[PDB]
Amino acid sequence: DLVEEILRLKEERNAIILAHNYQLPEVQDIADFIGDSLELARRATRVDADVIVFAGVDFMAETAKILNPDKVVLIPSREATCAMANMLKVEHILEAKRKYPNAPVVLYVNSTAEAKAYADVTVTSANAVEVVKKLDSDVVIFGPDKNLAHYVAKMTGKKIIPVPSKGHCYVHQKFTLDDVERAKKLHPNAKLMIHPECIPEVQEKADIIASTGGMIKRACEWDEWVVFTEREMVYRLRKLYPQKKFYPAREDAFCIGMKAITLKNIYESLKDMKYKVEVPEEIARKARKAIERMLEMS
Ligand code: SF4
Image (cartoon, rainbow, N blue to C red; front, side, top):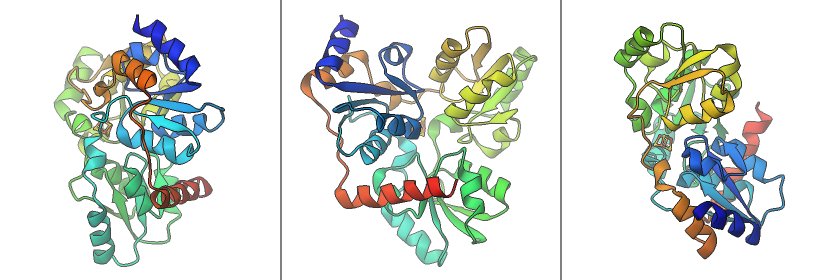
């Protein structure tokens, strides 16, 4: 029985399990903390665990390691990867800095640790506007998501240059205006909670624009919601709010990287102490400074 063995090994390893909101229900049920990556990493800094098992994708485990350098961070599969974060290369950043002289470089926290090391500051979707409004530049380099960049440009009035120019999340790009229309026909009493990684024309139809943490916070505002994000979030919301209704905007909105994590490989991760996530000291130092600036600016 995986669950029993996982729980026993978690105690033996002095480990905590951090699960992203898109993890399967059976994985979330054995997690200590559930949320988005930055809040998970920060919550781990307040406990004296020796090991973090990160049920999530590579860049999220990296953020955990950046904020918890004295803990062993394990990712159950190195195939738990983020296509959007992987679109951005260091060369994209250096080239953009050359093309937009002196413009600040802002990195969405959904990004690799290496990319954060070239950032002046990081942002979450929830603090991106507040942070960017404090940059005294009409032009801002922003990556890796062009769709969040559009939202930031709209809310700040600044010229936001996405890096890379076509960076985006393939999961959230699946949502279309037809999915909006289908939702309104089938669920006329529902409101639409839409992730800022969705395309601009879909964002425009939202009742709320929110990351997963904001979806949980603002779900209290209505009794029925159609959810424009990765489909496992619906189960997360249903378990949090059993008396509300939540429906996926698309049944096929599936992050392959997130589903690389299984009960079986969480068991194997704890049993064998793999796969170790490391962040080079200099990259970690610079990524840490960009995260610290984000707190100072919000
Ligand atoms: S849902 Fe998109 S942005 Fe999130 S981990 Fe998957 S590919 Fe990356």
